[PDB]
Image (cartoon, helix red, strand yellow):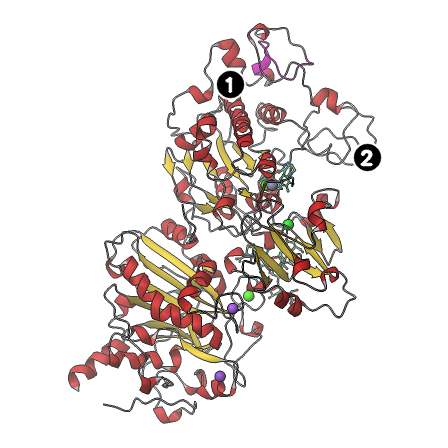
Amino acid sequence: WTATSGSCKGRCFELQEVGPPDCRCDNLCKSYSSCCHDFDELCLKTARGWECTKDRCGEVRNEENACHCSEDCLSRGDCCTNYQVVCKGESHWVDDDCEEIKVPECPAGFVRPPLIIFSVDGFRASYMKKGSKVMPNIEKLRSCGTHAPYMRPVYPTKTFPNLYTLATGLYPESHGIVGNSMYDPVFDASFHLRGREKFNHRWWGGQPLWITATKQGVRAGTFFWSVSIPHERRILTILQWLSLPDNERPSVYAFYSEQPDFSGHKYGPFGPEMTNPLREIDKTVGQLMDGLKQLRLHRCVNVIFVGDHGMEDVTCDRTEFLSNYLTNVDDITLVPGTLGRIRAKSINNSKYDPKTIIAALTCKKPDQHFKPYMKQHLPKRLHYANNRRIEDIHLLVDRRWHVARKPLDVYKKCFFQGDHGFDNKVNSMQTVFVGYGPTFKYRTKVPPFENIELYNVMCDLLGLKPAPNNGTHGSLNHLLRTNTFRPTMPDEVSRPNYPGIMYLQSEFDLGCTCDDKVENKLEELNKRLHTKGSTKERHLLYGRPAVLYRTSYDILYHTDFESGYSEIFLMPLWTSYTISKQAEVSSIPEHLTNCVRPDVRVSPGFSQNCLAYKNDKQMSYGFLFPPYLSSSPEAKYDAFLVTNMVPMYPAFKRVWAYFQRVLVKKYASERNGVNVISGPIFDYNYDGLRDTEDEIKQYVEGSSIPVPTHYYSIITSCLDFTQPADKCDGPLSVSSFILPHRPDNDESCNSSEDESKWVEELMKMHTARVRDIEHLTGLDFYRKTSRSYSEILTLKTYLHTYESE
Ligand SMILES: *[C@@H]1O[C@H](CO)[C@@H](O[C@@H]2O[C@H](CO)[C@@H](O[C@@H]3O[C@H](CO[C@H]4O[C@H](CO)[C@@H](O)[C@H](O[C@H]5O[C@H](CO)[C@@H](O)[C@H](O)[C@@H]5O[C@H]5O[C@H](CO)[C@@H](O)[C@H](O)[C@@H]5O)[C@@H]4O)[C@@H](O)[C@H](O[C@H]4O[C@H](CO)[C@@H](O)[C@H](O)[C@@H]4O[C@H]4O[C@H](CO)[C@@H](O)[C@H](O)[C@@H]4O)[C@@H]3O)[C@H](O)[C@H]2NC(C)=O)[C@H](O)[C@H]1NC(C)=O
Ligand SMILES: Cc1cc(COc2n[nH]c3c2CCN(C(=O)c2ccc(S(N)(=O)=O)c(F)c2F)CC3)c(C(C)(C)C)cc1Cl
Ligand SMILES: [Ca+2]
Ligand SMILES: [Ca+2]
Ligand SMILES: [Cl-]
Ligand SMILES: [K+]
Ligand code: NA
Ligand SMILES: [Zn+2]
């Protein structure tokens, strides 16, 4: 119930919410149907429109007008935004020369530069170039401020997940807004774009920026704008709040535009109808900037111009139907469109079987335009699994397509020509970032970065301590003139043991054999020196990784590689080696095919054994340092140490062997040497974080050898590829992956073919940031470089995406 008989007189766009059944005058009142009877009349004035004209200059104030051109409007704070231009011979902001803002130039009483977040829905990254002739205000912000060529959204590349990620710094799996439509089985409640459940606070997790600010004594404007409030009124409202007394005035504000997304859905990302929405958004930006200039705030406020996601060409004809794959289509509920999520229609149907649904959707038609996954098998870079609102069965839809349950859903719901929601590495899904103001840099281009990083920066801009989030605080310091955050490297928790030769060969009963009993003071000292670390500078280029949790591990040195060997997990946590451009690839000799050698530095009790692999009919083994890349036939023996062995399904060995035998050398030849760090990952609870031992669900049969869920590699070289990886004086270049350790290659529809036709495609899909691997291993890389720590943080957030320009 709402008693709508009170009044908004003096209360229009009041900042604090009053509680039912009292009548409201804030932004949300319309969305709850709770506004006072006179809200429209008093608070949504339109008379005479949004612009001063010459005849209005110096007019007698008429309070009915939407905005004012009377002499008293500046002190009231309610001039039309072009007042000074029309009536006082001032220039529009866009027509002024760019001039560096070296310090905040603010009115007296301003404690800090305000922040205005100007969010545009569906604003694809390439609009900045492609729409540049029609967006002069935006283009000035971009060229004079700090900009990225694009900003990476989160998956799914839909509005609510991305706006809430911008507000929180969290992945959707952690903030809980995992789609624009959701079912929460604990709640037994559904969230939709239409209707009321979406207003319930239980959907919205984490701590959004307005809460962070309010808790730390920094006031905030509303972020949500009711759809019926026109853009011109949202801008004037912001500008009126900026005229409040010091003790009442917010320091952080948001504007949202539903354009150009609304038109993009109708017309496609580049429809000729798109030029006008872009012009209209630019005009709105000009209204704000002229408005700020009238308030003497245009060299005071930090403005962020940001999108939520891009827009792709998608039409009704490019729809795949589950009814063409599944016999049982009426026993499922599909969340459809540019992604799929499947669950049982009834929890009382015990004949529902996810395994049979996955198989019925796997590589069934030659050009099939979606791929099914159990959510734990999705690329880890998506961070799209650890939430009960994400269904176990996921469908990754190809760009330009939709998935639906039955054809009738598509014609009983062509209209649309654009959509979005696809994998967040797809070029059409990328969006925009510009920062302009005293705290941002001047005329500066920065590399592309992820939207999860922005919360920390916005906190930095407001002097706030960010709530715990998925940004890497400091990785965006290069965007900022001041207010940088200067973190320390985390402390190493476990220090390594450095074992020498402590065991005789006969103490081992591992069931392993090797043909290695074949015999010099020149080369006896030389191999002692290699086992004590004499080539370590070559193979460990960035210091040893720090172990950030309590465990027991050993550093093992070898001619060709160095490793950190876990006594708990019976394998390396990491294996580091450098391959020069000149390196030669060799074979595993016939006589060494099945060779596994005990490591006399490590106890039998802390070693794997070959018998377990014999007895486990599903599990085989590989090696982390590849025997193919040995520096000499004698060094090759090191690669067959039991301490270099890891458990591998035969299907995965196809992948791994191709990576090690062909791709590593390819990379070294393309990048002028590479340093490779490889290792296992255990994430059985799909939380993105390193498992403890008691979380492992699978061991090599009859042993305590845990089976990884993934294998990673970090492949580092010199950004200036004229210098070799091992003698690089400047910035680094990295690519990484987190490959799923699967017992089949069902993910790869062409896996019956030679590995040259499918393995690299798989590896590209599972590209990763170093930071992703850090979370999954509890390791901290790049501890000893010549580079600044903020630069290294940026490097650790880099994602190699494999998309063209
Ligand atoms: C991305 O950044 C985020 C933020 O830093 C990282 O997420 C954090 O990771 C921590 C580890 O997973 C996690 O810490 C746990 O928190 C429990 C308390 O949680 C509540 O309070 C916090 C603080 O205010 C709040 O934020 C939480 O919000 C979550 O839950 C509500 C729903 O209730 C949602 O609205 C909200 O969206 C959010 O959901 C997300 O997180 C939860 C997990 O908290 C997931 O289940 C959801 O799917 C969703 O992702 C909560 O309201 C605390 O109780 C935990 O402590 C247990 O574990 C420790 C191990 O140290 C153990 O020693 C303790 O004994 C304890 O165990 C007991 O509980 C077990 C489970 O019931 C039980 O099995 C045992 O036997 C014991 O009884 C733990 O500290 C932290 O909450 C989240 N925060 C957020 C916001 O998500 C994230 O990891 C980053 N991602 C990557 C890839 O780096
Ligand atoms: C800067 C900022 C602003 C906001 C305010 O955002 C909104 N204010 N007003 C509307 C919104 C977005 C959703 N609405 C839509 O019209 C809509 C459009 C497209 C698609 S689609 N089809 O493009 O996915 C959808 F789904 C939609 F719902 C309703 C209008 C937020 C929060 C978190 C408060 C939302 C966080 C931040 Cl950092
Ligand atoms: Ca959107
Ligand atoms: Ca885990
Ligand atoms: Cl969705
Ligand atoms: K086996
Ligand atoms: Na296959
Ligand atoms: Zn949209």
- Horizontal and vertical percent position of residue 337: 63, 50
Q: Magenta segment: does it hold 21?
A: no
Q: Is residue 667 visible?
A: yes
- The residue shown at (52%, 11%) is 86
Residue on which disc 2 sits: 21
Density class for disc 1 (Cα within 10 Å; few <14, some 14-19, many ≥20) is many
Density class for disc 2 (Cα within 10 Å; few <14, some 14-19, many ≥20) is few
Q: Quadrant of the C terminus?
A: top left
Considering only order in the chain, which callout, 2 or 1, is on the residue closer to the N terminus?
2
Q: Magenta segment: does it hold 66?
A: yes
Looking at the image, is 635 positioned above or below residue 456?
below
Residue 586 is left or right of residue 331, and the answer is left
Looking at the image, is 45 positioned above or below residue 337?
above
Residue 9 is left or right of residue 464, and the answer is right
- Horizontal and vertical percent position of residue 288: 53, 25
Q: Which residues are magenta?
A: 63-75
- The residue shown at (43%, 73%) is 654
- Going by the picture, which residue comes out furthest to the bottom? 506
Residues marked 1 and 2 touching at CB (< 8 Å): no
Residue on which disc 1 sits: 294
- Going by the picture, which residue comes out furthest to the left? 522
Q: Mark 2: which amino acid?
A: Pro
Mark 1 residue element: helix
Looking at the image, is 83 positioned above or below residue 287?
above
Q: Mark 1: which amino acid?
A: Gln
Closer to the camera, 583 or 439?
Answer: 583
Residue 709 is left or right of residue 796, and the answer is right
Residue 476 is left or right of residue 283, and the answer is left
Count the labels in the image: 2
